[PDB]
Length: 282
Image (cartoon, rainbow, N blue to C red; front, side, top):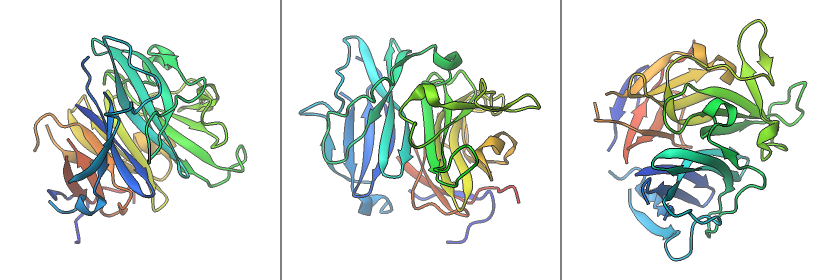
């Protein structure tokens, strides 16, 4: 239906959504003390959602087992064409111990860790234990193949968000991510600067109608918010649409449906679905 700018309405432990052509997976973890992937009935993601299966109960969902006393939790998704990468952050007493990349598969489990992708929790000033990313194939001087833009922050929600970019070719090598720095002395491939001072949490970023759309949990405000910008490097200057306020008690999540429109995003929070026509910089 027709929604007004900024108008949001409700349609009807830690989980993350991975979208494969034939299956939507809800990868959920414990946070205490395995990580499983629930097959979501796509027909039910509108009917005020049912599941048709689960991966990771019999055989494990991840190839690397969980160290005793630790917990492996999903912490962001990057989709490059049809390659799906999930960040898995292992915590101990809820303190992040390390983060790694994992190649997600739809039909089976035993998801393999991306070779060489493990980093301790202190990596990059502790602002790369939670991420979201999207691929823009538009060529630029530095890349004929485009860029995977990646927003990152701390799994613990105590740090602001920063922006990296990687060529689709080189994304799997974390050491090749180029941080974005604002300011006269800034630019790409520099120690990244906070997009803005608020302490952020979980993020979902996607290009809709050529627009960078970021749905995130703002921990400073404690609300599920949305930002729309023309380029990710301007997300800090983007207008904010509050989606879930505190409306619902202690929100968390904010997954942008692939079938979202620039004037009608469908955002899942926890799962409840919200339709929001966000404020746009024009």
